[PDB]
Image (tube, rainbow, N blue to C red; front, side, top):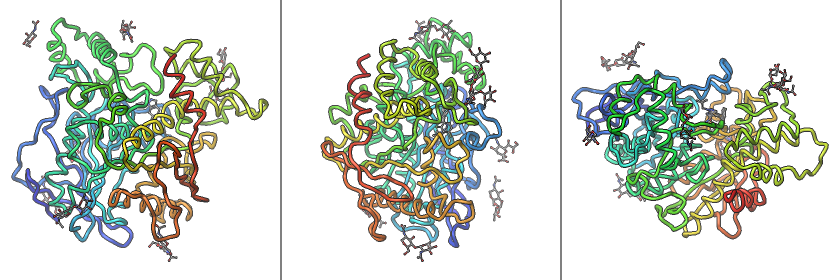
Length: 526
Ligand SMILES: *[C@@H]1O[C@H](CO[C@@H]2O[C@@H](C)[C@@H](O)[C@@H](O)[C@@H]2O)[C@@H](O[C@@H]2O[C@H](CO)[C@@H](O[C@@H]3O[C@H](CO)[C@@H](O)[C@H](O)[C@@H]3O)[C@H](O)[C@H]2NC(C)=O)[C@H](O)[C@H]1NC(C)=O
Ligand SMILES: CC(C)Cn1ncc2cc(Cc3ccc(F)cc3F)c(C(=O)NCCN(C)C)cc21
Ligand SMILES: *[C@@H]1O[C@H](CO)[C@@H](O[C@@H]2O[C@H](CO)[C@@H](O)[C@H](O)[C@H]2NC(C)=O)[C@H](O)[C@H]1NC(C)=O
Ligand SMILES: *[C@@H]1O[C@H](CO[C@@H]2O[C@@H](C)[C@@H](O)[C@@H](O)[C@@H]2O)[C@@H](O)[C@H](O)[C@H]1NC(C)=O
Ligand SMILES: *[C@@H]1O[C@H](CO[C@@H]2O[C@@H](C)[C@@H](O)[C@@H](O)[C@@H]2O)[C@@H](O)[C@H](O)[C@H]1NC(C)=O
Ligand SMILES: *[C@@H]1O[C@H](CO[C@@H]2O[C@@H](C)[C@@H](O)[C@@H](O)[C@@H]2O)[C@@H](O)[C@H](O)[C@H]1NC(C)=O
Ligand SMILES: CC(=O)N[C@H]1[C@H]([C@H](O)[C@H](O)CO)O[C@@](O)(C(=O)O)C[C@@H]1O
Ligand SMILES: *[C@@H]1O[C@H](CO)[C@@H](O)[C@H](O)[C@H]1NC(C)=O
């Protein structure tokens, strides 16, 4: 029941899963609370305790604005925090198999949410199933989001940038010093994350301070080279200063500004974070990762291009309809409550939403590449086009470009294309296979027979969980026993990927090839 960690003893709880027993250590601190003077600074090493910490409830989530676009709707509220918001939020969770493992592979989860929001305590991140069914140890951590986690005055240690990334990294260090006490193999750690979490995992591949803290990496619908993923030192400053004006903290001494923002309450900082950008989109990362010179020593697209990353295996993939969810967060003519058939004029007005500071020619060039119809009278044409535009530009093509460039340095890479729509999905059907809705299959929620998934879904979760755990254990996401389709390596030439669905699991080649040539070779010029 009690584990001795290097900072003190922690007590866990017992959980019944699938006629077995999993041990959960929920809410173990991994750093001093970043309060007061420590607000905006890097996380600080935690002082020993001599009690027994009761890691028996999820700890506080980090301060964050909440999605209030669909109050009472489960499809949006299931992602909102489900513990108290607090600045005291640097805690982590450990799920160990019971009976205690001997030398188990560790899976470390990093949640997404645009670097502004998220919490490990979400129901779709519950690692008890993975512990039970695969005998891996699952770790997740809370890390600071928004300006409290990524406010940047570059060079200044009072607000150096990337604090939330350093939070994550301090958690990975925690696993290194402590997971062996829990039966875990620190030499066998896989990071996996989704969206901003997956872009975080991709940055830990780049950051030299993380290189000895994990073995392998899984990237779900997200990578650092996505257009929302990194903030420039320019914008980071303009946004750090805009926040200072919006709170009356404008000073001539940069360090005095920070001191001033420390005496503001978390809600005052949260309430002004949206306005630091003049034109925002539904994909607006107001305070995100930056090239700080510490966690990130150069611009990441240059490190990628020139082979400057941890050499190891990666499992990368995306969902079929990544971009549809964002259309009801602002695009004209759209609603989760009608079919959202839009017009050519409605489509064009929607590009101005998602590409605000882009030239008229750039927006015309998006329209041109995405409105050459297989049928001009199909009434869903513009509705589906804009979703693909958002999805290809923001997730699918950056994920493919990352895998391409990363594999070019001789490491095994595996790409998937998740194309199964959940049977219990509360969103409308024109939204398809939405951004974020593989996560429950990865965590094995369809395995519980008691929550109204179909049988075909339990099998698909079962296969995904096996492949995921075989990747973590053996760098190879195969399912070797049940005559499963073999998952080939992704190579720069042939570009083979695995489709994930409940019908046929197929080997295909060169995903969204025509669309990504536009986004990756042309559009970065405009
Ligand atoms: C799908 O739904 C959207 C969203 O509208 C909202 O949700 C619907 C399900 C209904 O409950 C609506 O009452 C509700 O507002 C519809 O988009 C909206 O279409 C209306 C059509 O009248 C637009 O209103 C007009 O807009 C112009 C702007 O120039 C004004 O001149 C007019 O006075 C008038 O208000 C409205 O702007 C528009 N809003 C948004 C956010 O898109 C959409 O028509 C609908 N699609 C369907 C039913 O296929
Ligand atoms: C609301 C502000 C605090 C931030 N904000 N503003 C616009 C917007 C749009 C999204 C997109 C989205 C929403 C619901 C969903 F079901 C799937 C989705 F893709 C998200 C988001 O991603 N929410 C959680 C889903 N996982 C993947 C992280 C967040 C957004
Ligand atoms: C491979 O297939 C076997 C069946 O041959 C699967 O075993 C099932 O396991 C679940 C959970 O223990 C049981 O409810 C089922 O009844 C079993 N099937 C049978 C036919 O008895 C196994 O899970 C599969 N592995 C995968 C898909 O990774
Ligand atoms: C920490 O936990 C101690 C034991 O918890 C209690 O006893 C065990 C056997 C379980 O039944 C558990 O659910 C009970 O709550 C407490 O006695 C102790 O006070 C706790 N420390 C705190 C609350 O600071
Ligand atoms: C635990 O195993 C250690 C070796 O780890 C091995 O190599 C890494 C790269 C992983 O892929 C992992 O699966 C392998 O087991 C030993 O050095 C260590 O002594 C072992 N400790 C035990 C058994 O307590
Ligand atoms: C940099 O910031 C400038 C000022 O920001 C805007 O104006 C003031 C009054 C604040 O209310 C702030 O929130 C506003 O958004 C912008 O004018 C300028 O364009 C910015 N440069 C960028 C975004 O590249
Ligand atoms: C945000 C916060 O600090 N929450 C704390 C809660 C609440 O303050 C109370 O339950 C009243 O809401 O109290 C605890 O003792 C508890 O019971 O877990 C500790 C926990 O950290
Ligand atoms: C800004 O203030 C700090 C102490 O808060 C000091 O070290 C620094 O020299 C100051 N810079 C000025 C006044 O230009």
